Amino acid sequence: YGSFCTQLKRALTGIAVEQDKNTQEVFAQVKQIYKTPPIKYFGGFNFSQILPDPSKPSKRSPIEDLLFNKVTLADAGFIKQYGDCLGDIAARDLICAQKFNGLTVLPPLLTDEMIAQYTSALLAGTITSGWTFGAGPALQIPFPMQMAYRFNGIGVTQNVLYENQKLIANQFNSAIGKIQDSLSSTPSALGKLQDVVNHNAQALNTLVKQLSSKFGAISSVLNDILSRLDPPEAEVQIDRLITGRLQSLQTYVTQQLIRAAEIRASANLAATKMSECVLGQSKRVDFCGKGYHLMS
Amino acid sequence: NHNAQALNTLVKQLSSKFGAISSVLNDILSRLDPPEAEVQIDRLITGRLQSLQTYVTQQLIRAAEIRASANLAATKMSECVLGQSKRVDFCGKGYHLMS
Amino acid sequence: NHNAQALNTLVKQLSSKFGAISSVLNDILSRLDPPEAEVQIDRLITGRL
Amino acid sequence: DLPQGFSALEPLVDLPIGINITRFQTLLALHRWTAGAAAYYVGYLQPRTFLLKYNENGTITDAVDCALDPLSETKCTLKSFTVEKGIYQTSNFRVQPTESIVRFPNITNLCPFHEVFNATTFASVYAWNRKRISNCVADYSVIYNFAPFFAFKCYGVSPTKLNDLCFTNVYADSFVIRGNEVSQIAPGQTGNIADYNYKLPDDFTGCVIAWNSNKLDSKPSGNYNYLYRLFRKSKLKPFERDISTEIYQAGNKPCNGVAGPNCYSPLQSYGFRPTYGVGHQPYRVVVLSFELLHAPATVCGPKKSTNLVKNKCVNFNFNGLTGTGVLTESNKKFLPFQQFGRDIADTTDAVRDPQTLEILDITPCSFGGVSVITPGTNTSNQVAVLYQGVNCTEVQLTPTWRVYSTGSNVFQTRAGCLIGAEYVNNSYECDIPIGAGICASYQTQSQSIIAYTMSLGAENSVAYSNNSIAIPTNFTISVTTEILPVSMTKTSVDCTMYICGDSTECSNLLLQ
Amino acid sequence: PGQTGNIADYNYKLPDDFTGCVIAWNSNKLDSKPSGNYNYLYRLFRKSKLKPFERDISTEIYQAGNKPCNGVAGPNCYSPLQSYGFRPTYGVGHQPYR
Amino acid sequence: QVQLQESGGGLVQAGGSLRLSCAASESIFRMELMEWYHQAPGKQRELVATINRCGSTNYSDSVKGRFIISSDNAKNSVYLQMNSLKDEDTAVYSCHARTWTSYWGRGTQVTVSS
Ligand SMILES: *[C@@H]1O[C@H](CO)[C@@H](O[C@@H]2O[C@H](CO)[C@@H](O)[C@H](O)[C@H]2NC(C)=O)[C@H](O)[C@H]1NC(C)=O
Ligand SMILES: *[C@@H]1O[C@H](CO)[C@@H](O[C@@H]2O[C@H](CO)[C@@H](O)[C@H](O)[C@H]2NC(C)=O)[C@H](O)[C@H]1NC(C)=O
Ligand SMILES: *[C@@H]1O[C@H](CO)[C@@H](O[C@@H]2O[C@H](CO)[C@@H](O)[C@H](O)[C@H]2NC(C)=O)[C@H](O)[C@H]1NC(C)=O
Ligand SMILES: *[C@@H]1O[C@H](CO)[C@@H](O)[C@H](O)[C@H]1NC(C)=O
Ligand SMILES: *[C@@H]1O[C@H](CO)[C@@H](O)[C@H](O)[C@H]1NC(C)=O
Ligand SMILES: *[C@@H]1O[C@H](CO)[C@@H](O)[C@H](O)[C@H]1NC(C)=O
Ligand SMILES: *[C@@H]1O[C@H](CO)[C@@H](O)[C@H](O)[C@H]1NC(C)=O
Ligand SMILES: *[C@@H]1O[C@H](CO)[C@@H](O)[C@H](O)[C@H]1NC(C)=O
Ligand SMILES: *[C@@H]1O[C@H](CO)[C@@H](O)[C@H](O)[C@H]1NC(C)=O
Ligand SMILES: *[C@@H]1O[C@H](CO)[C@@H](O)[C@H](O)[C@H]1NC(C)=O
Ligand SMILES: *[C@@H]1O[C@H](CO)[C@@H](O)[C@H](O)[C@H]1NC(C)=O
């Protein structure tokens, strides 16, 4: 029938490489891993709700823990050992059915611990250095002075902060505190991240279920066709199944290509936001929040 | 490299039988009789149409990606070259001077 | 213009034989026998899909 | 020894021998006798796949075997003689079965096909007989010895494959019809026989056997013992008979039991004579109808039943259902009337043993994918092999080459297990990505091809104090480059030349 | 091509990719006798099926038991060369065909 | 299942002779390389002798004129014929073979009394 399968494999391999490229581009802006000082006192600002928690083995901040627990995952790409499928617990899930038909899920190159380390490095750098660590060597500065200069950036003089430090610190602490409860209470907060998993699972399940159609033949099982018909009268039946399954595979591959393109666009936007709102201050309207931007 | 590979694959697709008895139309026309030839020619026609459709769709997707890249390049030329940019890490690493 | 052209082409595609003896299902179901009509209806179904 | 290099071989002679050959022999010439000595090399060919290279002169100057080592398999897959640095996917690995098992019921009797195919009398078409066959071993190769017909005519199956399948019940219908009405005994047919006397369903699965019987059903005066129905209010439903005899009415007034005007008898007798044309001579017809497997099977051919094995990748044949897999014990609670078990993809996964009423579960044998990690061929010929998504305790395998495990060449990662690489505690930048936080590279000197954990970046820690600042005292001007694609190649394609060429019939076919 | 039976796998076997023609015609007026033609034979027993375009000529006493035949057609010992019985009063399905 | 196993080590007086018999479980006609390494206590391993598929044989400086390496084709094995033993030849000997992945033997002890 030609070389359709080489094309399908090439397309899927390209998408698989593109995903790792997206993650690496987004999360790896800085090439030095900074450490926060042992003593946590930044003029009254409470950063304990975003800095890593050393007590837990995972070394993740409480908000990161809430986000990770809020989004469920279907397949993590780990060792789905054949022994588990053969264990015969009388509960045959969809993963074993997908595995038995030649569809597999590969694991990402960057484990969650590495991403957490990258995020913690970025947070420590932007807390102890300001925005200088994104344009050269990291230069230390006290946090109230950095806040004064960020205030001066938006057209409000410095003396507004130094005479209102306690009130601003309390407001910032309360605003940070309300975020966790807002995330927990809302049921559909993380819908964008869940839709990806749901769509991929639906596509794979539809591809698996497509195997039970006749496509005009006398049976949907090749062994029955081979054992019930003459040697030269079975090709005219097998051809219909082959054509139908090739059509299904082509449809799945095209859909995956389009979805990958959209996700790549989103990843590029996220990388731009990270480079412009985190490593510096932005004067663009409604790009890094609503209002006058200070930091992210 | 990608364009050359696509064209070469499209050319090489012409040597497949697609279930017919031969991949050359002259052999099919000169061996079988007028009424039957069709049941064989239709297979080749369908296969070649499928190959052409696949190639066209792939070209469309690649063209969309290249257009996105070209738009980004035009924006970079308008902002970094014809002026100075205060956007961080848009026109180089560091503080921008010119391009 | 593009949307209208796409819709008009999709409508006009219904007048092609796709290798069958006729492009109207009633003619195929009135001229040929029950067990033979299928080999003709399948071509139209595949083409329209 | 045999010299290095390549030299292709060219054919001379092909002959139509057409005999068994199992052994051969070499002759020698001895002068007279006198002493002598000879030497010769003998090798055995095997079915292989090669990649041969032709130079500009048309001669074969190089070849690559595709089943010698992972590098050669990668070269064959890429269709090239050079491989660049990276990780490629080459093939899959599967476990082949060991033996075969067959399980058939406890059937000893022989099916009674003799009493059907000749009984010196056949029932009329309007009231046809019907015999039910069950609980017997069916031999369809003896049917040819009972009736002088030409060939079968089967719709759902093939005549030569009837000795393997195992059915639930068989039905035989017999009658006598006219010569030109035989073509009406088929699915989707309309005629006097089809819709008034004997109607076949649209999804028929069986065979039709019709043969001429002019020497038994014909008389010089004329046979009048065979009748058929002519008038009927409505068409027949599939597999239905009518026996009732009455006076059909074709008018408004009632017949009142007399065949007067608009009153006829819907039972016309065939007139059979020995001087008629072929299309009018009597034909004896027997239809065999098969019932597929939904209940315990009862009728099928003479296949021996072997022993039952478990926990082994084996081939199975349960009542005509053939496959390969691993059969284990079952915790499923089958109902008494159930015999099979189906899954999401609608394939059998739980079966009931025909001899002992026991349930078995089927699982496909182990399989997986293989990736080859290699540096450039310009550097070295050594590779590492990654079995994807497999606990590295499992590893007749499909690939021809076999791996041998030493103490330290086998490593287990979260993406499978890696053979031919050495693990180290050092952390460098990633070179050849493998899986979850693992990379591989080539060492200077399996000692070569080391696998390590990728390093995020150099460690740092900026001193922070609430009365200290750091101010630069010098600058540096830097110039960097950034590359961006803009446009690609513009191509145009011609339909008629690509699909059909200079042919005219193909273009006419494509026009529609 | 792709047929199974006595003739197909024990006497004459055709390949699955056959490219040719078959010509068969009735010869009842030449190959039939009132007493019965016995000059045409066919093989009945064979250990294994025939490869395409392969013939067999050897005449031997086929063994259907564990004990050796020892050259006598006794118990579980037969002759795998059965003679066609051709008569002019047979049905069409039994008449000889060339 | 193990690729290579060596045998022949023991106690031998100075000036004697010995034979080492590294036997492989795969056809040696595709191994492309058979190497002998010796490690004495206190130092690292050092190359001893090398034989390749074509037939070329190589030795290091402290080898030539003392002992040789050969191989027969009746049984899959590589033989090293230790001759003219001296004190520093006491070491553990290993055999190595690389087709597309290096296979290492267990090694055997060789001690010479002086
Ligand atoms: C910064 O915020 C954290 C969490 O809101 C504070 O930790 C709380 O401390 C009080 C008293 O020390 C405890 O009763 C709470 O249980 C703590 N919260 C949690 C979640 O454990 C922390 O004290 C704040 N920083 C300062 C300087 O007050
Ligand atoms: C800032 O850096 C520049 C370049 O790194 C310094 O200029 C160098 O000075 C040394 C010592 O006089 C010369 O040997 C080099 O040739 C100079 N480099 C160039 C490119 O001219 C400069 O001195 C530094 N600033 C200060 C205040 O020392
Ligand atoms: C291929 O070559 C080997 C050695 O070159 C052959 O030698 C046989 O090796 C086996 C394994 O030890 C012995 O059991 C036989 O007795 C050897 N044959 C002899 C001594 O004549 C052998 O023909 C092949 N070995 C394989 C295929 O493993
Ligand atoms: C190819 O053939 C030409 C003509 O004989 C000859 O000159 C040339 O050397 C050949 N090339 C090779 C590689 O042998
Ligand atoms: C049925 O078969 C034979 C033909 O072989 C037929 O002549 C006869 O009427 C029946 N058999 C017997 C034994 O009567
Ligand atoms: C069965 O009964 C109905 C009811 O009278 C009658 O109309 C019909 O013709 C009969 N036969 C069939 C096949 O329905
Ligand atoms: C079938 O026969 C075998 C052998 O005689 C016996 O072991 C088995 O119990 C029988 N099963 C049934 C259902 O008759
Ligand atoms: C692999 O199998 C071994 C066999 O006992 C087991 O100890 C181990 O936990 C398994 N590992 C994984 C990742 O399945
Ligand atoms: C690499 O790290 C593991 C974990 O501590 C350790 O057990 C292993 O011995 C290390 N490698 C070497 C060569 O020591
Ligand atoms: C920050 O200020 C506090 C005053 O409350 C002082 O105790 C502390 O030492 C200062 N930080 C450093 C690093 O000296
Ligand atoms: C050829 O000979 C072998 C051994 O004598 C035998 O098993 C086989 O049936 C014969 N015929 C064919 C077609 O192989």
Image: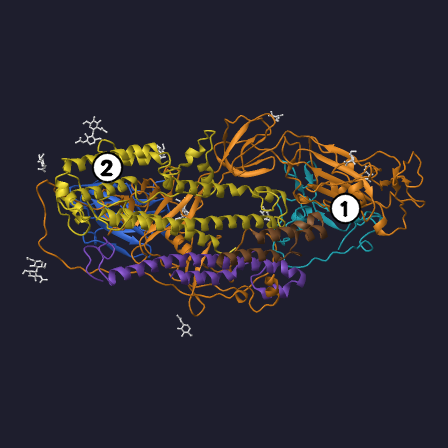
Rendered image: mark on residue D190: 1
The answer to whether D443 appears left or right of A165 in the picture is: right
**Three-letter residue code for mark 2:** Ile
Residue A163 at x, y percent in the picture: 12, 39
Total labels: the figure holds 2
Give the SS element for disc 1: loop
**Chain ID, mark 2:** A
Residue E26 at x, y percent in the picture: 78, 55
In the image, the chain rendered in purple is B
Q: Is residue A143 visible?
A: no
Question: Chain C's shade in the image?
Answer: brown
Q: Is residue A53 above or below residue A247?
A: above
Q: Is residue D359 above or below residue D36?
A: above
Q: Is residue B22 visible?
A: yes
Name the residue at 34% across, 50% down.
D373
Residue F8 at x, y percent in the picture: 27, 41
Question: Chain F's shade in the image?
Answer: blue
